[PDB]
Image 1: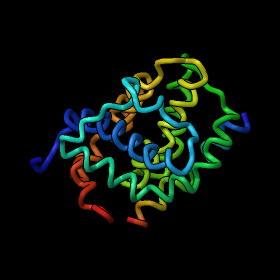
Image 2: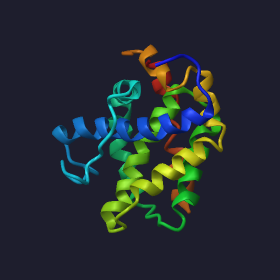
Image 3: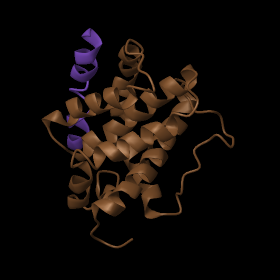
Length: 169
Length: 22
């Protein structure tokens, strides 16, 4: 794509890259384990749009945060289970987790991490029985990101197109 | 309660270390 980017485009790329990112991370994980696995390869799957430059973004992010994720993933679900959030306070809780994480600051590593645990927390409720949490989580993420000045940060770092300019690029 | 601070204190650990491993 082209250089530069505004919060407007950042939001769209965020949701897209978010779904694709979590999709890849969990995709490769399905081989090793099945923790918080998706709804099987079907219509309920995560039909991402890898045809765009964003497609490569999620993949890369999953790599730089692959070991890190799985590393603190086992424990992530452990404590997450002790939470047991709801669809009413879903955002009330999520917003807290992120705010507490990015509280120290904002960095490429923090962004990827947010999504890593994001999908987990989402599926946690979805599989629990609250069918239809994917959209809720995604919406809260994009809204929280564009509210926590996150979008602006990403745009300054070179939008989501900067992922290819990272470690494994 | 203990989870409210724990769930946040546990993420002391996913934000940083990737940025340095990239």
